[PDB]
Amino acid sequence: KTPTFGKREETLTYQTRYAAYIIVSKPENNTMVLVQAPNGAYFLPGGEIEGTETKEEAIHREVLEELGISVEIGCYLGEADEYFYSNHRQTAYYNPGYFYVANTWRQLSEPLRTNTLHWVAPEEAVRLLKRGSHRWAVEKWLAAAS
Image 1 (cartoon, helix red, strand yellow):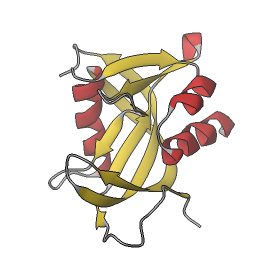
Image 2: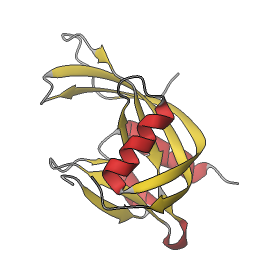
Image 3: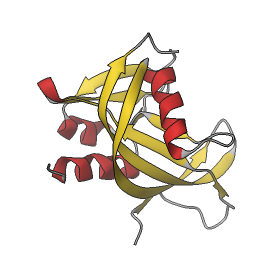
């Protein structure tokens, strides 16, 4: 029932790590920002929850590090899960993701800068995003009216 994405390997044992992501949009020109890794993969802003962080605290840390922004976290879109293999970790991960919308945000600094930032149309984000869980979040947000 929980939207689930990613080819999982029946051979490997998956470790669980939780993640939180947020849609950060520029309503005035109908764009939203994506973070593109050095390897070329596009992601929503956010990431794996660390230490004793809440989902929201992980978001606050990530958008500062990646985007140089603060956010006012708004709507909770829901959970979408991702199965993947981390090459650098050499570890298979089960990744419950918790997806949110920023109501508003503020530019505070430059990003803390191996990734590149791309402001794109939401429909273009859907075409660029690496993960089915991320595409799911954008499509849900697109369908969510006032």
